[PDB]
Amino acid sequence: QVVKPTDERIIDPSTANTQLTGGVCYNTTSGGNKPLAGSPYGYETWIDTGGGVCSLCWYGADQGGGAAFRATWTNPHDFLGRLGYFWNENKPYSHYENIYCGFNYTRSGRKTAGDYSYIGIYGWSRNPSASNSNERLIEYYIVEDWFGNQWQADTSPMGINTTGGTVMGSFTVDGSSYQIIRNTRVNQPSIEGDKTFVQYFSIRQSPRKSGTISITEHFKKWEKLGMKLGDNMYECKFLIEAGAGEGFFDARLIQFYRADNEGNILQITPHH
Image 1 (tube, rainbow, N blue to C red):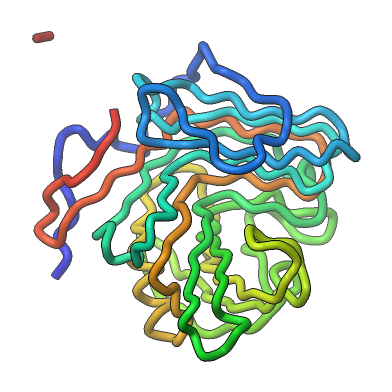
Image 2: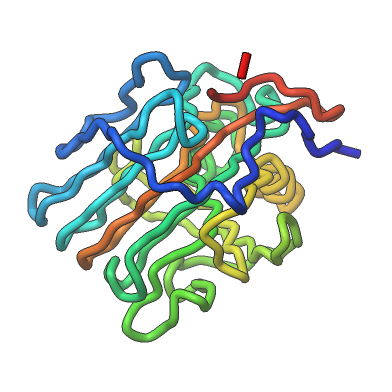
């Protein structure tokens, strides 16, 4: 079928756990994607000035897989820090072939990120020809982990009481079942202004802080359930989102790579 890449440039996430230094930090809302020097990636921050101090610090092009970052928040109102591929060039997900992300991070503990929080992969896509106007804009999450809250352990996967919406199905990939959820955001803020749009989630049933995410596998399973992504992928980034609380996220590894079905590398970052 799809051959898992074995290219030696891929960093084993399980043992990629050395603390990084020399971050470059951003303490305010970026106003969208901002390209990173000497990198294929871009970052984005949403730091609501109604709340306390937040930051995202990129570890640079030449260590940690190239997309590693730290983030901090002190009583935010829905802090989002993210870094990874920025696309928005009128292409469907399949144009990018098999997308993978190897990761390894530390984070603050249970109940340090408010009542909801998300760690994993995030983006948007556009599908203007969709018959249902609600489905012409999509926000998406592949949720590897979260901070739990007062009511629920961070070792317990979030459900529809947190995400909203409807369980569509599930599947198993990368060592865990994932619950697939579709939610409609009615007259809510988006990359296209206040409107109605849909959210797609895959929630990892066994939360984790390191491993590899076979991102394209999620996209395929969503589309099979009728959760279509359309023909203009916006981005595919590694995200930390914190509803509130005082906490941190600190990646030793975030490495994106893309491979075709034979498993040959199309894109990867970064003598003895």
